[PDB]
Image (tube, grey):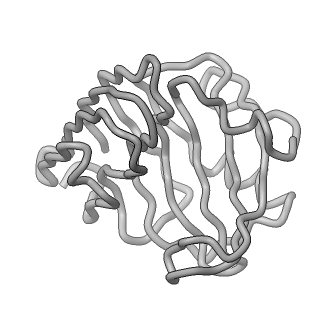
Amino acid sequence: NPGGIDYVQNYNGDVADFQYNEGAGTYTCGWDGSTDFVVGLGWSTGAARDITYSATYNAGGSGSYLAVYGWVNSPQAEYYIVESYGDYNPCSNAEGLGTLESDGSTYTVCTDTRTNEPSITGTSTFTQYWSVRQSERTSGTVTVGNHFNYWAQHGFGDSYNFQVMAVEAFSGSGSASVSVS
């Protein structure tokens, strides 16, 4: 599959009309609701790989991200590299970790703790790492290593779980069509 894609991310995809094609490295979704979902395509084992995407992403008025999304097992962490988003900047009420430069833009970097929250191990305590692109875009390449390298200076581990190019929303409405490699 494109870029060795071998994984379909499907959390609550049933509220997001989530449809995919692993062989083509494509997916679509469309939403209008107040339930959280995270859907997309990628790799069952994460790495500091370059992720190329091309999207149409329409999330005006929506609490939504277009993002590289994944987890690390130990210390347990959930991470996002946000390329475009809707109404809600996730670094607004988080702890600031400065900025970094990657793939043509500055990213705002931040972190927060989720205590005893739904996670990949059921219910657990984990750290979120966010890089939020200052100049939003819908196509390009994410040099994931740049983000990993920076977050690792602030406690981020390297035992990668899954890693995908994702669309998440939790409020409002939108549509997306994404190609990944």
The image quadrant of residue 167 is: top left
Percent x, y of residue 177: 24, 30
Image: 98 above or below 140: below
For the residue pair 110 and 139, the one nearer the viewer reads as 110
The image quadrant of residue 133 is: top right
For the residue pair 137 and 78, the one nearer the viewer reads as 78
The image quadrant of residue 170 is: top left
Image: 1 above or below 24: below
Q: Residue at x 66, y 22 (%)?
A: 105
Query: Count the marks: how many?
Result: 0
Q: Residue at x 26, y 53 (%)?
A: 13
Percent x, y of residue 180: 30, 41
Image: 122 above or below 152: below
Q: Residue at x 54, y 72 (%)?
A: 118
Image: 147 above or below 75: above
For the residue pair 84 and 94, the one nearer the viewer reads as 94
Asked whether residue 9 appears in the rendered view, the answer is no
Which quadrant is the C terminus positioned in? top left
Horizontally, is 75 left or right of 121 in the view?
Answer: right
Which quadrant is the N terminus positioned in? bottom left
Q: Residue at x 73, y 24 (%)?
A: 106
Horizontally, is 150 left or right of 52 in the view?
Answer: right
Asked whether residue 147 appears in the rendered view, the answer is yes
In the current view of this chain or complex, which residue is farthest to the front?
34
Percent x, y of residue 66: 45, 35
